[PDB]
Structures are given as structure tokens and as C-alpha cells.
Image: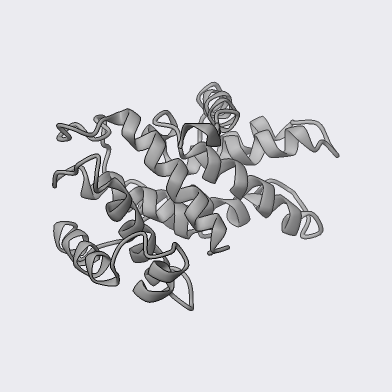
Length: 229
């Protein structure tokens, strides 16, 4: 049972309470734009499901201390995606494969120097429990057999990764955000009803609080207007 560890180092997550408070120019709404962009970027590269959720973590951290400009959010957000693939995936995309695949959007040298700034700003500790980390772990704990895991991990991740674009979920336990996204998925594709609302209520401990997350995850997911970027 790796849920206890998860719940523990999940408490080691900075309770923002102020998504980008230090930001002058850029605001919470420049975040929704940038994350939609980063999401598209991570999808265009078919990177691990953990790369996007991890870059979001990096991003909201970096920008919780240093300052960003509307004109550099893509550099910053691109660097976050680089930093993230470099730590999770086995074959961590290079600054090169990231400049050419996105058609010299920035010079191979600018990301280099942007990545570094972020690593420095974050004191070289880029690591985070991502809602993504709860799918498999809560899948069995939810009495769900390894026959529907492969398809449940795809939709649940797609939901979560799309939901994390919203500044709502950006104030939740990665655990909860993984429950509501795991639920909103089993909902749309029902093989069994949703009695798991109680079953999960013991893992992440909560019952009326584990519902609101669902209403927020699913509400946030239904908010992916690629037409905002």
C-alpha cells in the first residue's frame, strides 16, 4: 500500500492559497492560457502522463517566487515541460528535440538559460505527487480488477490533465483531484454504478468533501476551449 506514503509526501506540497500572488503583469488568467498551451505541447509529443501535471507543479512554484512577463510565459512554460520530462520519463526530451519539434519557437539557447533559472529558483528540488500518481494506486483499492485498468488510466489521466488547466483544481490535494477525475471517468463509462463514492471515502478519508472534488474536476474538464489559445 503506497497510498500512505503518497498521502504523506502529499502533505509536503505547498499550500499555495494564492495562485501566482507575486505576479504583477501575468495573472491567474494568463495561467489558464499558458497551461492549455503546455497541455497541447505535451500531447503533441505524447510524453508520459506525468510530464504535464508535473510541469504545472513546477510552473506555479517557479512563478510563486520569480517574476514572469506575458511575453515569456511560453519560454517559462516550455522549460517547465522540459524540466518535467527530464525527471519522470526514462527518455527525457532534450532542449533540442523541444526547439525543433516546436519549430524554433525559441532559440535552443534561451530554453537552456530558462530551464536553469527555474531549477535555481526552485532550489533544484523539482518533484511532486501528481494526481496522476493516484490512478493505479486507487484503482485496485477501489475493488476494480486489472482488466479495465489500461483504459481507465487513459481516460482518468486525460480528464485530470485537462482539469488541471483550471485554477480551481490548483488548490486541491493531488489525491482528491485524482479521485474526482477517476470518478467522473467511471461515470461517463458506467459498467457498475458509483458506490465507490463511499469506498474511496476511506482512502483519502472524507465523504461530502470527496464529492465536491468530483464536481470541480468534471466541471473544470468540461472547460477545455482550445479556442482560448
